Image (cartoon, helix red, strand yellow):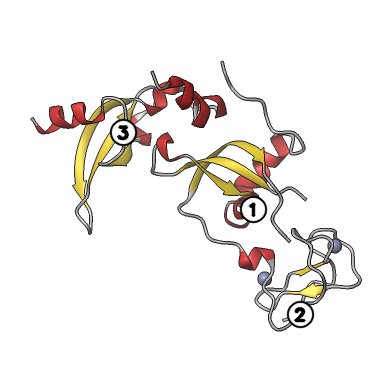
Amino acid sequence: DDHMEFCRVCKDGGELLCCDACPSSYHLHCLNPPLPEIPNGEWLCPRCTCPPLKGKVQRILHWRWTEPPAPIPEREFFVKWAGLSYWHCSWVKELQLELYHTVMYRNYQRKNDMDEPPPFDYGPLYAKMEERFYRYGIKPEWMMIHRILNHSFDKKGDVHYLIKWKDLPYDQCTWEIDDIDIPYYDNLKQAYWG
Ligand SMILES: [Zn+2]
Ligand SMILES: [Zn+2]
């Protein structure tokens, strides 16, 4: 059960600080934020400290820069979650992706530039729907309801509906929450029940 004899971030050896939960080892200048020096007691590495993901990510859409944590800028990615529709597209931390979706993460890496974010895809509440969604690569039909196919009740009992989304094949239907203001949503709910 040895540790890495080289900093994970910079691949070089020397003064190393080793995680007590995993064999990772880092150079204090390499971590973000950098640490003053060797801390007292246990120390868990940035990949051991990393929080788990809310679900499983289906597709990475976009990435952005963010403000450095409080003592180098980190990075967040706009993700499409597997099983949930584009209304649930969230932002996740770069190291979350590498830890839990490595091959997918590195596949994205190989294709694009990771110094400058990709350009926005421009081709009522549209001006905002363009803000959270459309510019990142979400074709606006993918957030429009085509059909309500079925309903379901969970442990708590909040009803879920299985929605077929427009210009998105049935294989990517999605169980959606009751309390979300989709355009038209409750009008199709009444059609389904009535
Ligand atoms: Zn660790
Ligand atoms: Zn290093």
Q: Amino acid at mark 2?
A: Asp
The image quadrant that residue 154 belongs to is: bottom left
Report how far apart the C-alphas of labels 3 and 1 lie in the structure.
33 Å
> Which residue lies under the disc numbered 1?
98
Q: Secondary structure at mark 2?
A: loop
Labelled disc at residue 16: none
Q: Secondary structure at mark 1?
A: helix
In this view of the protein, which residue sits in the foreground, 117 or 55? 117
Looking at the image, the residue that sits furthest to the bottom is: 41
Query: Quick check: 55 left or right of 71?
Result: left
Report how far apart the C-alphas of labels 3 and 2 lie in the structure.
53 Å
The image quadrant that residue 10 belongs to is: bottom right
Answer with mark 3 or mark 1, whichever residue precedes in sequence.
1
Where residue 124 appears, as percent x and y from the top left, is: 38, 18
Nearer the camera: disc 3 or disc 1: 3
Answer with mark 3 or mark 2, whichever residue precedes in sequence.
2
> Which residue lies under the disc numbered 3?
181
Tell me whether the residue at label 2 lies in contact with that at label 1, contact meaning CB atoms closer than 8 angstroms.
no
Looking at the image, the residue that sits furthest to the right is: 14
Q: Is residue 27 above or below residue 138?
A: below
Tell me whether the residue at label 3 lies in contact with that at label 1, contact meaning CB atoms closer than 8 angstroms.
no
CA neighbours of label 3 inside 10 A, class few (<14), some (14 to 19), many (20+): few
Q: Amino acid at mark 3?
A: Asp
Where residue 18 appears, as percent x and y from the top left, is: 76, 75
Answer with mark 2 or mark 1, whichever residue precedes in sequence.
2
> Which residue lies under the disc numbered 2?
2
Q: Amino acid at mark 1?
A: Glu
